[PDB]
Length: 142
Length: 142
Ligand SMILES: [Cl-]
Ligand SMILES: [Cl-]
Image (cartoon, rainbow over all chains, first blue to last red; front, side, top):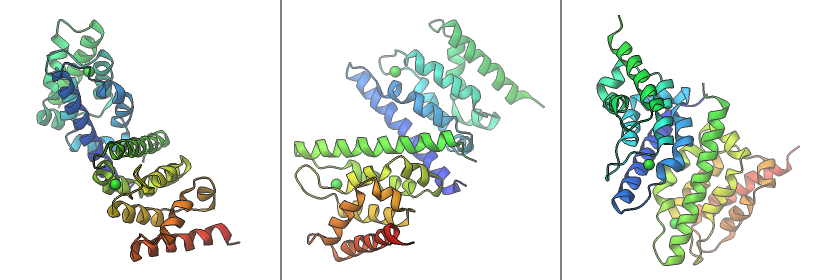
């Protein structure tokens, strides 16, 4: 009932939107100023990233690189706001992420960092460990 | 296939996106800067406005108001680029627009103007006349 061309178009559009917001936030950080792009769009974007109809296309289109980039340090090396870090981990957790996606994305690297990062809340560190445990299970299960 | 929550979220998202681009282009025009938001997004936004899965929600959510907004004059009274005018008319004609929709949106007013505007191409006046004919037929059949 949604055409495969439409699912693809919307997945691509979401990808490009995550990239534009990332790049605008990073450029603002480099101008000594607040990045508000991600915080203003994370709920709505997270909601859509978790659409079960869209996930397979989003995953196949490398959406994990954008999620990754949103979890990464800004130019001044501060971290994205805690609501973003929490919400995007909650997105990775509910997505049907399998071995193929990890071996291709680098996301497991940023997530792993969160799990052992001493500046991170026990809550987030915990949730990143859970993700790590789950993804170890994907990668290695018979 | 797609949950009704997600359909409604994508429709609202597209609505606010058309509004934001319109207001940004209108504020650029008033400054003396070329308006490029609409031209850079009309193909992709058009493509999605024509999604059959989304149309009923988009229409119910008043998307005709935004389409109307994009067809009307900039602050200096010049018209949006011809590619936008042609593409949004093509969107209106393939979209399943009925009596209720017009009744509440004012888009029929902007289309009627295009049909009688002497500053407008023959092909554009023609397609707007066709739309008017079709909408007169919608409004009036038993
Ligand atoms: Cl941030
Ligand atoms: Cl324009």
